[PDB]
Length: 135
Ligand code: NA
Ligand code: NA
Ligand code: NA
Image (tube, rainbow, N blue to C red; front, side, top):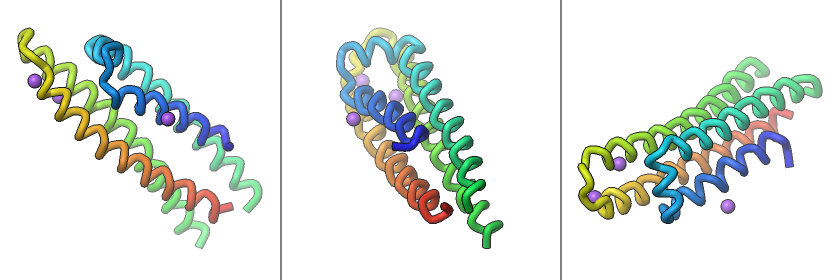
């Protein structure tokens, strides 16, 4: 129930919706709305994570653990940036189609998103584990 976990949960719920590639998702993927909204949720998650670590350091080998926690935090942020970037890519590939069917592009986006989401989830679990043993 930590603040950064709730923020990550909002990013995660939003991305679970994007995965469906429903009509309204597809509409908002060709505007900047999905990637703008996900970036805001990403930034919030990272901000709350930074503040949580800072407060944990008040209730605490340490050097190694602190560097490993930094690396796990950076992985989470890179994962979220990779998701946003893949969705920016999709918008460009649609435009290149010049009005032609995007069904194949959507099948391919859906399968790639599943794998990016798998990576984000496993990195979030690893980060949560390191935060629990840091404290
Ligand atoms: Na969900
Ligand atoms: Na694409
Ligand atoms: Na296509």
